[PDB]
Length: 342
Ligand SMILES: [Cl-]
Image (cartoon, rainbow, N blue to C red; front, side):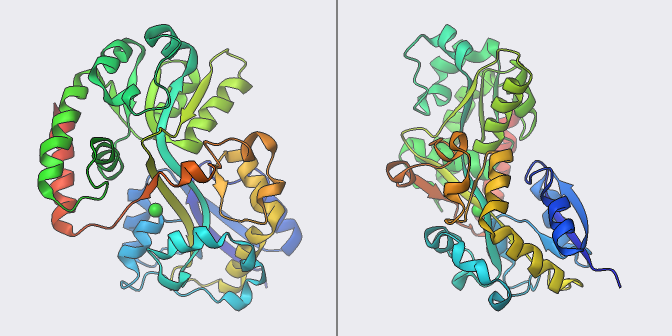
């Protein structure tokens, strides 16, 4: 009988031939579906009976569901290359998944500033503060960049944390007043200069020159940069992990508790743990993978990019998302609607 495997992953988060290569090597039929919204994935998981054997949630969402019985523990004896994973990244993911019981770290990155090098330098000068959140969180700078286009993510959790860190508050403040007060105060001063709040349109807009500065996910900004280079359109997109720090986050593979094809799922996970497999993915999607054995195999342009693989001094400035109580979640959501309506 045919062996089958159903995977649900983000768009633009695998190499073009990863699945084909796996099928050639193993004889397993893969059904590979994609989503571009975390809201979509989580709704399906909470409803249950998804039909997926492997899914790719955020590490933070995993914490919220470790008690909901959504996932089943990973049998590490079926993953002999588990030893290839970076122990430091396992520790960070274990903040949401104690003892790394349910999740295999896949890729990770930061939320920083993507920008058009030429347009930012034209408007703010040669010494534009591209190494600082000042570039996009000082109203005086956004007023000058307004005409060339400014985008923020449509993501209250990441944007509020970014603002709180910049203001010198706890990035993960549990104080409702921090969100409704100082954080909202700054966002309302910036708001008239922001063209839109959206978590994917900025990728193509950066690549085509339609916006000049964005809050964005590192690898997606690097994808925009590469798309502009492949189009030979002369647009120069870069990305900055600013000097004040930034949020780091981790996407993981996990196995729904009702998965029908568990043996095949473990074959695919151990396939991903082979160093060349995940290095090849990083080469194509411009995200750092969590496999320490894989790093030397990654192309120089990606591995040596400190906005993809940050060195120790930059990693020390990164913070991670803490899961908040529902009451803070709702304050955050309410305040974000007010910010956007401004
Ligand atoms: Cl995360």
